[PDB]
Each structure stands twice: as structure tokens, then as C-alpha cells.
Amino acid sequence: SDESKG
Amino acid sequence: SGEQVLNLTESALIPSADSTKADDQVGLNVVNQTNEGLYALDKDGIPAIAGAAEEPKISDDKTVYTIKLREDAKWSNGDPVTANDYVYSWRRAVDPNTAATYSYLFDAIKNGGDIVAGKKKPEELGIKAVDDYTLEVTLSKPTAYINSLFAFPTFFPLNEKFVTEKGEKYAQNSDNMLFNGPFELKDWTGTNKKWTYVKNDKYWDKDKVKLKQINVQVVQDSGTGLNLYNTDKVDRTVLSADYAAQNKNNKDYVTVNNSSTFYIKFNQKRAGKDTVFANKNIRKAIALAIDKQSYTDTVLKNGSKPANNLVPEGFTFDPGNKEDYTKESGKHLEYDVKEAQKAWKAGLKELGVNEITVEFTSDDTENARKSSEFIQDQLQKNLDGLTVKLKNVPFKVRLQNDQNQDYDFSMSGWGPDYQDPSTFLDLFVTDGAQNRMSYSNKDYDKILNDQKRWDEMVKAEKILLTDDVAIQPLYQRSTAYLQKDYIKNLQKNPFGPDYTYKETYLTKL
């Protein structure tokens, strides 16, 4: 899964 | 004990809630609460039967799976969940018309590869409705992690009648979704900053669901999150940079190891024209010029650590001797200003230029902006004549621009969908839907297309990183939170969709 930068 | 309502935050608007098309951690986490496949990860991280009524019958050669389905499973409109819903959705996933980025996972299913390539019809896919509550699934070859695929949203069933009726508005908001999981989604307009999970009264296992409601709001800076946590408006909040460091000794501080890798992507072709990153020396210059240790110590401060591998440490191990993939692979593309500057001078000479401007894409959170400013600082100070413009966009826009190759270089991340190195390595095969860099190495493709399989996967990482500098791993991600002590049984999944709230409950007061 593509991860978001928090 | 007390009211069973949980209040959470998320760092980004939902990019997709279509279980076939979604490929991001935000959307895949949503559909994991609202829908369910044949298997779902249990409390120990093992796939366990969910939509399947019992353990399948499996052929001697381990390629044919005969699966009985629950006869008490229902959609949120009362329609039964049948074998036809799985046949429909798996055909949807491989159908070229759908252009689902995860269609490649169906390489595990007989004819999946051929169908994605338009060589066979979607109806040829190796899934059959033997009757309304029995599937026969035929694999392309034995697949040790097949049950992890069955637990992954792309393999969930869909109600053909409902999907067809909604047409291009399907899954664009919570009114245009159907649910077969522990929760229904409410209050999501498609583009808003709040959404809600409500206990699904038509879920077959609803007696194990304890939360009546889970409220989610978008929060993109730790200060805002922290104030909401301290005023009891949220029960769990993400801490980044100094907010993590200032709260690391708090009783309620927790750290989650995500087994995810964040890396720089180098787009080699944009709008049909080679970019500067088509030059390997230029990729190498940027790659080696970032102090990864300082990055994690300054920007993250949350348990994250430098990465010198695409595959994260502590995740996958050699079937022969049980040693970590990363130990066998060794380190690649280690921080080195001098070697970076060597590559930079040589690249600039090859291109016939003295200066280069490139745009760095990342997300629009406070911490992503800190991250981008740090990387800009590192590259500009170390590489004379380099300008780095910053673009800091919503997660969904970054992903759209990624799919379109409308970027120069970017901060991206991947979390594993199953426990094998291929979940990471398969991204960078030629023309892969998660490549989007115009990176192509036929030796790399040949490797990825049992002990022998493992050994070759180890070798593949050297090609990707040391030899080609296709990407640059930056860090292995951990996430810090304050978490109220009254949250019990919050299941963090080790791969696939991040959380399962199904059996979470609260012991308030």
C-alpha cells in the first residue's frame, strides 16, 4: 500500500 | 465499560474507497472496516477464515482451492453475499477497462496475467462459482501467501447489481458504497474532512463488534491533534518531530513499527521527455547527498530509523537459515557527501550543464513540509548549482501525479501487503502500475518474473539500488502517538490494511 507522510 | 464511541484522527483526505481501485493506506484502512473478504488477519497477524465458512479443500499440488462461503453473510441492503460477488469483483480487478493498479496481484490466479495484458477475456480468470455458496479458485502456481491475498481488499467481493447501478459515481461517497464488514461508512461526501464508522447490524459477526461508532477527522499538525487529545475530543493522536520528543516520556505515549519504507522516487520521463533523472549519475548525486541519520533525528523523532534497503529490517527471513533479508542484502546507497559530489560533477558534465532545477513532491502536513525543507537544505548545500523547488500537496494529488508521471522526484512510501520481499520488489518491474518512473531493467524483471526464489530476490535489491539507483530508501517508518489508556484490543495489522477495529472496545471510567 502507498503510504502517506503524516 | 462506558460509552463505546471512539474518536480518531487521520492525516489526509481519503483518496479512494473503491475496494478494487484503492491502493493507499488511508483508503485501504477504510474499506477494511466496512468490507470483508474470504480471510481476515486475526489477533496474531495470521489470516483466518472470514467470508469463508470453513477451511478450504486444497488439491495435492496446492493450486486448486475449493471454498465454502458463509450462508449467513449479507450486504448492507440485505442481498446475500454469494460466490457471484467474488467472481464479479476478481474479474473487475483484472479487467483492463478498470485499470486497477493492484491488478498485478492477480498474477497468483490462473490467467490473471494474461487478462491484464488483454490476451484473454476477464471471464477466463481462475475463479468459478460452483454454486451460490461455493468457489473454486485455481492458482497460476503454488502461492504460500495466498491467504494474505484473500485478506487484501482487492480480493474482497462486490455486489455487481449495486456497482453497476451507481456507474461512475460508485464509491465516490458513503451513499454510493455497500458494506459487508463490521462497520458501515457514513458522513463521507467524497471530499470532506470527516467520516464515521457505525456498527453494521447486518454483519454476520456483529455480536463480536463492541464499538457502536468510530468518528474520524482529518488533522495535519500535531499541535492541533494534541489540543484535541487534551480536551478529550480525540482518543489517539499522532505526534511528530518535537511533539513526539516532548511527549516520549508520557505514560500514554506509544510507538508503532509500520514495517514500511519511505524512499525517494526518481522520475526519468515527464510529459514524454527525459528528465535529468534519466542520468544515473544525477540520481546517485541526489541519493547520496541526504544525511539519513540527521533526517530521522531531526524531522521524525518518533522511532523511525535510516533505511539503506527497500525491504524493511525485521520483516522477512530466509526460508533456509532464518536470517533477515536485509542482513543478506547488505546496505545500499549509504549517505556519502564526497561520493555524491563525484556523481554530481560527472552527471553535470554528461548533460552539458552547470545548474539544474527540479521540483520535489511531498504531502501537505506540517511534518511533510519540515521534511521537504530539510531535504531541500541537504541537496542545495551539498550539490552546487542545484535548485530544488518544493511542492507539498494533498496525499491524493501526490498519488494522482505519481500515476500520471507528472513529477520530477518525490517522497513516497510503501507498506507491505503480505510477508515476502516481493511485495516491495515487484513495484519496480518495467511498466508496473506502481513504478511510474520509466525505470526499466530487464535483468531485474527477469529475476522477479523456493530457496532459489529467495536467493534471487536478495540479488534483485542490489540491481535496483546499488547498480541502477532507481530509488533511494530514506527511512523505515515508525509512528508515535498519545493513546488513551481506555482503548483496548486495537488491532494493528503487520501487513495489509493498517488496523482492524472489529473487536476494539473501551474501558472508560
Image (cartoon, coloured by chain):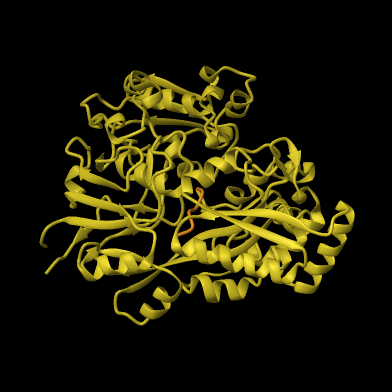
Q: How many marks?
A: 0
Which one of the lettered chains is coloured orange? A
Residue drawn 71% across the image and 50% down it? B452
Q: Looking at this view, is B177 or B53 the one in front?
A: B177
- What x and y, as percent, mark residue B292? 63, 71
Q: Residue furthest bottom?
A: B249
Query: Where B445 sits versus B218, above or below?
Result: above
Q: Looking at this view, is B44 or B469 the one in front?
A: B469
Query: Where B373 sits versus B166, above or below?
Result: below
Query: Where B167 sits versus B18, above or below?
Result: above
Residue drawn 22% across the image and 57% down it? B6
- What x and y, as percent, mark residue B224? 32, 65
| Res B430 → quadrant | top right
- The answer to whether residue B55 shows anywhere in this view is yes
- The answer to whether residue B484 shows anywhere in this view is no
Residue drawn 53% across the image and 37% down it? B102
Q: Looking at this view, is B353 or B35 the one in front?
A: B353
- What x and y, as percent, mark residue B442? 78, 41
| Res B169 → quadrant | top left
Residue drawn 11% across the image and 69% down it? B509
Q: Quadrant of the N terminus of chain B?
A: bottom left
Query: Where B107 sits versus B241, above or below?
Result: above
Colour chain B appears in = yellow
